[PDB]
Length: 13
Length: 240
Ligand SMILES: *OS(=O)(=O)CCCCCCCCCCCCCCCC
Ligand SMILES: [Ca+2]
Ligand SMILES: [Ca+2]
Image 1 (cartoon, chains in turn yellow, orange):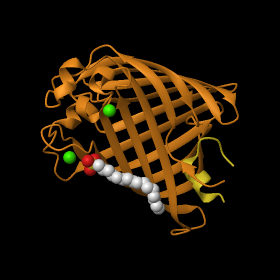
Image 2 (cartoon, chains in turn yellow, purple; image 1 turned 30 degrees about the horizontal axis):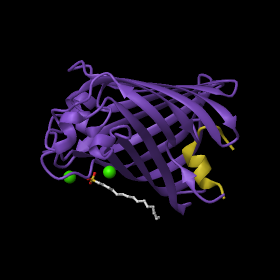
Image 3 (cartoon, chains in turn cyan, purple; image 1 turned 90 degrees about the horizontal axis):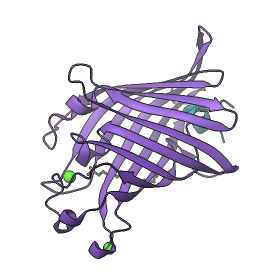
Image 4 (cartoon, chains in turn cyan, orange; image 1 turned 180 degrees about the vertical axis):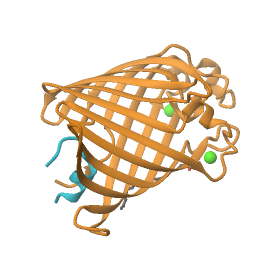
């Protein structure tokens, strides 16, 4: 979740 | 899902106002360099350690590559004019600090190397310690990336005269369209550069993309060179 967040995306799996 | 993007990934066809043949006089084909080039950027992020400093932190790495390819110059065997290689190592944090409607979402600190992989005399490189801060508010995204040059900069000792000490990034989501602006500006020397973009989805993974760059520091070999470049092509991911 979150649009544009590089870090939030990296935390995902 | 397998690989993570850092910055944008795109391939466009471009035309610059003037090609910097001087800086590249060392290459035999330079005298016949053309103003039209393929420009593309690949940018990946590599999470190495999730949870290093908490549930929402990450020790990570990234790699951004920008290339300028003289495709139409068959006379000279269509050489690459320039590639910039930009590896990074950073600590990232996913945050939710809200202030005046804006939410700080990303806090990133790390080390950046930016070089062009050439030997002398066309060698260009610098090292930076930086922080990247990203905040959003509605259809807006703003990113500030201040830095501190460290180490040797002998290949271009005056690079900060043209690049300054920060990069500002503004995104605007207009429906599925993304308007973007990316820039640098040194107040004390008057030098800077700006990159305006517009993208729109053709499909869920591909976007049409138009870009206009104007000013100094488009690439390392043109850090002290001023040009205006326009381009059209495709994009995978925009900034948001
Ligand atoms: O600027 S220069 O010093 O002249 C050239 C610097 C080039 C840096 C090379 C970095 C390449 C990164 C390769 C990415 C491979 C991804 C694998 C990562 C495994 C975790
Ligand atoms: Ca060739
Ligand atoms: Ca070099």
